[PDB]
Image 1: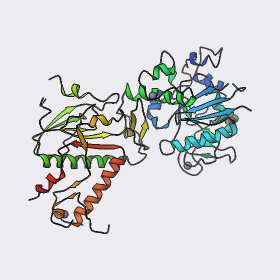
Image 2: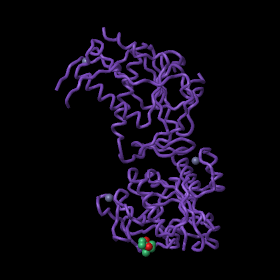
Image 3: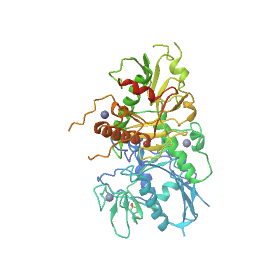
Length: 459
Ligand SMILES: C[C@@]1(NC(=O)C2CC2)CCS(=O)(=O)C1
Ligand SMILES: [Zn+2]
Ligand SMILES: [Zn+2]
Ligand SMILES: [Zn+2]
């Protein structure tokens, strides 16, 4: 059992207002046929247009909410809405486009999906709250058949062109008119009571209902993300490398070691309370400090309340020394903290839109993160960039321009002239730092933190 059997039953109650008389007894095999598609007993990689919840979770980067609302059915214009915010009007003859025939609408759909998905996934998964019109509109822009490869590269084909009779992936589909072998899932099959809005609004207040198809498309995908990444969590699912994952993760480790080491050297805290990932390792193994760990898994719904993490009777005295919250999202950090907090508003191919202001950050594993909130940092200040090193000044073993910087905290810079080794290491660190910030991470520190206290750690 890897794919969804076409012989699986499909509940049709949600479809009977657009499709009156629809049989209660229905399989995906009969539904696909009713949608105007012929599967021809083909064992060529595409067993079903519909996929399981587990297959959908593995392809969350491909998710595109899709809704169709009757503007006035083959006789009336249809409003096609996508979770990208696009509304297209198709005539049978928050962006809102005027009514156009299907032969031009389908070209826009291919362009939109290709621009949205080329850097995210090798496919598309239409996320539906199926009522009928969305399923019966698919024949006007979708073509199915055996799994194919792109005409210009090795990637799987996602588009088809009637002008050239060729197939393309999302990167090579300019001018293509059909979506080829898309996938889809109907959220209504998961067992819900009530309409889309009532279920969506239970968990999210950030997506309103402006009564347009793209609003329903957005709410549908948001509800699906809530069910699959908020109420249910699975950190055993791996996701392919699509960007700077490895550089970002390595940069995160370098910056954490740098910041914690310098905070310990500058303020000499006798104890450090490391709150977060139960599999955390000491980021500064040589530090003298008493290192105490507290287990908290990544919160995917609401940020942890500091009163629940710290209180109910451990060192007990979290007020002693410093608290390290490295990606441990809390409502309000104590004043004696070192914090790394992911900013959910960041635009990147790793960061997908999420539920109730939160975002779905996908880097090796999927992590739904509660909405970024500036008020969590009221007791702290932004951590300024700096590079600190106590290593000997020695080159060992890429051409040079001498480094001049007030933030290169080294013996050579104290002495008046940055050495080649510390200049190379400073530039590498600055690159790793900028990589982590641009990925969406934000750094915060206790107000007394001052890099001026680091200069006397070389004597
Ligand atoms: C003829 C069919 N396809 C087309 O319309 C091609 C794009 C022109 C109908 C739906 S199918 O089952 O994919 C075969
Ligand atoms: Zn290609
Ligand atoms: Zn929502
Ligand atoms: Zn040096």
